[PDB]
Image (cartoon, rainbow over all chains, first blue to last red; front, side, top):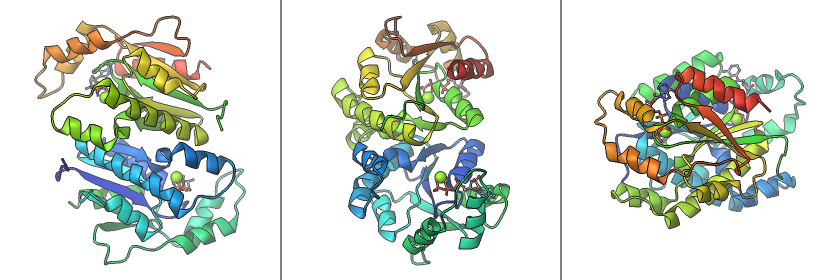
Length: 172
Length: 172
Ligand SMILES: Nc1ncnc2c1ncn2[C@@H]1O[C@H](COP(=O)(O)OP(=O)(O)OP(=O)(O)O)[C@@H](O)[C@H]1O
Ligand SMILES: Nc1ncnc2c1ncn2[C@@H]1O[C@H](COP(=O)(O)OP(=O)(O)OP(=O)(O)O)[C@@H](O)[C@H]1O
Ligand SMILES: [Mg+2]
Ligand SMILES: [Mg+2]
């Protein structure tokens, strides 16, 4: 049922760290399945969000379980499946891990100043520094004790992180 | 909550019509959001199918309702959203339509001989005739009364199918 020769990689990291760009390119070049985790939020969450209220860990819980389940499905028919999910808290990672031993994470790791300039570089985008601060505040970095976590250096042009991500995926 | 300025396109058609190959390349070229609808099956459907049994329409309902919420979520942040779902039965399509007035279908239309040839050209694939035959039996072509349906000619090279898809997407 779990297909141990198929693997799932959750692209994680704070907002602006490259999750969508990297994951978009990596799936293209690898012919891999690709799911953006934001699309699994229940109707409930989309409406809360539209109304400007910020989700809570109790709201994230149903979203994450659906993420879990979608990972379970993707691994039924693809050797390599990529999911985009910031996954800031260890506890979110545990919820994704459950029942998916063939799941691992690729942490797109960068420090604050690198990500900030990358967020600023978008024409017309009004940058609120506080948004990023909190991202980093919320971030619970996966340490070495989290052994299904691979880490990729973002202080690199898009092509590099894409390559490092590929290397990380192919490394076995 | 319905962003009436954003749109969702459900690429549909029988097995082998090209849904995946076309949606992939098209989302790539348009930088559109993309969801393979098979990834939204509830846990139980996956197991049921893991066990070798085919889904019945009761199984499909919650699958489709979840896909519906997924389209709902996608249109929140993407101007163009692609979803792959063969959606053969009118009923499945209504399930998708509900609460999504900004959703429409893109029918990858073509006949047996053409689809057959293509499935057969898969290297290593032992073509089983009955499969495709059942697909066509099950197909309830969207007639003119389904006004949210766009049609594309599959009897054209992939990249033309792509362009024709791109053309109907940009047509408005
Ligand atoms: N390594 C890179 N080098 C230069 N620019 C990059 C790199 N990676 C991503 N970018 C750009 O920086 C911005 C942030 O990337 P992206 O949208 O993928 O981040 P994200 O992690 O998905 O953010 P969010 O989680 O908020 O949706 C984008 O404009 C993207 O084009
Ligand atoms: N118009 C095209 N011209 C030639 N070959 C095509 C064309 N479109 C798709 N193909 C090829 O035909 C095969 C069927 O395509 P594809 O896997 O995208 O169909 P599908 O609708 O997603 O089928 P399924 O629902 O079974 O996954 C693929 O191998 C694809 O590479
Ligand atoms: Mg993103
Ligand atoms: Mg397909």
